[PDB]
Length: 546
Ligand SMILES: O=C(O)CNC(=O)c1nc(Cl)c2ccccc2c1O
Ligand SMILES: [Mn+2]
Image (cartoon, rainbow, N blue to C red; front, side, top):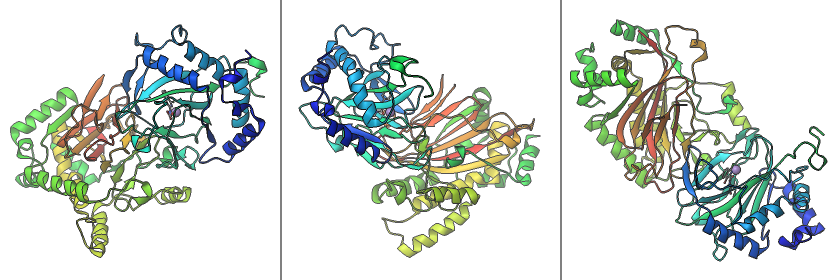
């Protein structure tokens, strides 16, 4: 058609504009990308927005990595059928011009992408409303070659930075290892397009949570590698960088023999006394133990309420609330200080944790390689010792004290005790043979994990006595309200590869799950709107049957 070029801003046909844009994309950071303002005929795009509002039904969908209002799921009668746009003539026209030979020649030229398919049209229409988000990903799927997003928020009002919903780009520490924190954030406006060549290991981006009751509407899509022969196209013409590691340390022979001897309520008065320092009387009585045992036999899981006793519940709630209220939480990995670490990389997870290992702050490749050449083991008492020194020098003020960290480490030490593992073996009739304990904090608007399976200990795979499962515990210490609906996120989700557990954050609960090879788990992204972080203690053990 003669009219296709005239449906765009005439600047994109100007050689001088094209060459300048090609150079800007070439020299962009943190990987090659670009943006064009006022792309399309304003009346056309306005007409498209009206059609969308009028004709398209959006359906909220939530997974580990996103919450979005989609229109594309053809498992909904509601699902948008791109083969039938009878009532969206202007949308039909928009797709036609974006995949035109004319536009593709311009666009492939400035992005240095090579040939682009005109027939492989690939678009979807979505809105992000309050709490909606999409976490870090690189778009690498199939024949996708260039990613684009055309923004259609209200054309007569400015989208503002504090609304959220920014497009964020993440720089590379090394290939397939994006930095945890983004280095650029685009605030989208009507008739702006953002785009980038899809680059395995590099083109990491996300959609910042929408923080207000506004509708962030977009059309997002891809240009693909052409079909074979299309316009003459001829084909052909990392676990190491994850922290913390999903690894456990084997227990001493002293411990393991204790558990065996017991399994072949046999705890002593002194052991019950020790347990009663932390655990509520309810769960140490003969009746309570029997109930928990029966529950674990039937479900291969426990969900305990009011796990810790009142003394320790009161202490931990106090110091955690004080820290929430009176201290400045770091919101960039560079600002995080001992004893905390940031989980990396961000296309897998982001949260703060205490593991008892020497301090690490991963800003460069050198930082990571140094850790990989010098593996060290957890030691929580040394971590405590280190905190005291830091703490004395500064002065232990309301603003800088480590009261929460010290109380939490004391709790970790309890769960590390031989006697606690004996109680665990009693509840489960399983013998722990390894352990990993982590204290975790999931900050509002930053932190999450994605759905993953347990990681078997490879060295133990051939041991017949060791169960093909990982026993996993979670002690939640989240003192704030408003979580019950799941709307603020932070819920612990266990599901089969159908949901086994879906528990929003709560105060003083203990979940215990025997995971076989296929069970998936994650902690959902915590909304910016949450009233505190999710705080918990995570425990994992290899087990043998005795
Ligand atoms: O909207 C934006 O600024 C960035 N959006 C995305 O990167 C994005 N990426 C993918 Cl892979 C999908 C995929 C499906 C639906 C929406 C998506 C999306 O908004
Ligand atoms: Mn994307």
